[PDB]
Image (cartoon, rainbow, N blue to C red; front, side, top):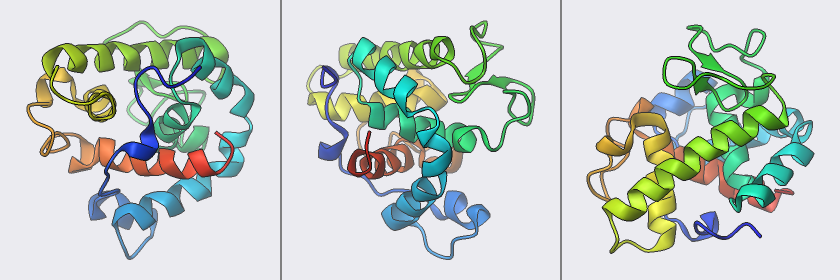
Length: 185
């Protein structure tokens, strides 16, 4: 089962900001930019599809959401050096920060993906308690936004991403996820 925290197809999104799209070599931004970048990572992503779907079922989170996060954080591993981000702080496909959590497992295995996803479900649970009035799908978006900037940065539904990296974290991840949803995740 994977619908415990909501469904990504029901989340409204404005996609990648131009700050995310331009460095990727696109001349346009928004949802189409997020989907094109997600398509570029699909071959690399498919290498971990079995593990991503397995962890999603295990934690009751959509495999599509895990894939969107992996695409944004590390381009499915293409941007990493032995699992490390370019500043040496982030580890693995989902980039768990070594200064905040001791990384577990190999950089591209089930243990790592389970750790990153558990960190995500903890943020979703925090937003659920912080905004009880929101719908489940709204809380899922808040949860994803907090994965980048912390629960303290989510003060409203409308402006949640301001303050995240490129001011578009959840919006961009949700769009990439909607793409993976249509392509096997």
